[PDB]
Amino acid sequence: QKGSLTIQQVNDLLDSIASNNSAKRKDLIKKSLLQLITQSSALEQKWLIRMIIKDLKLGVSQQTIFSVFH
DNA sequence: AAACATTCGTTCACGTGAGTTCCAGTACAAGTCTGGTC
Image (cartoon, rainbow, N blue to C red; front, side, top):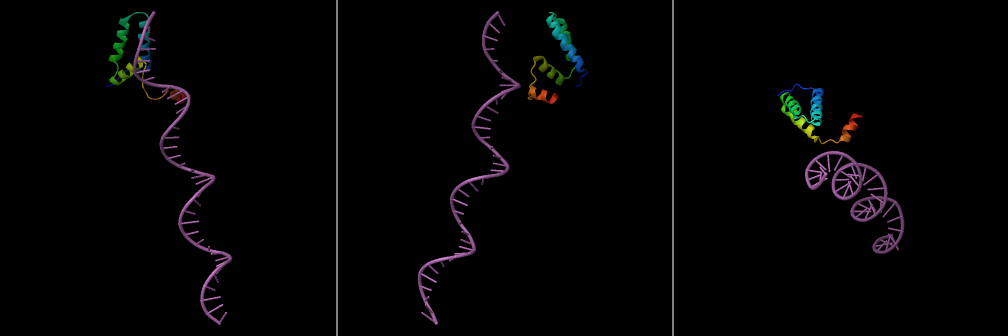
């Protein structure tokens, strides 16, 4: 019901997944995904799946996010 | 001298133009789903 991951850790794990896919090593992808699964809650994992597939469906336009930012 | 007609300022109802609020139609842009091959 509670996670123990920070944003930097998640970015590092995703970077490892991408790089190891580029290098044709699936064991490291499995290890990174296992760490993410073991150190995350169900909601966090749902959002991680959405981020991996690259579709969040927030309902707010990218232009709106940029306008809010600056 | 008395009765009737006309005129006048008033009154009401009804119709038309301009201002304001609300909603439907239109336009455009982004998001989402799909197709095909290498």
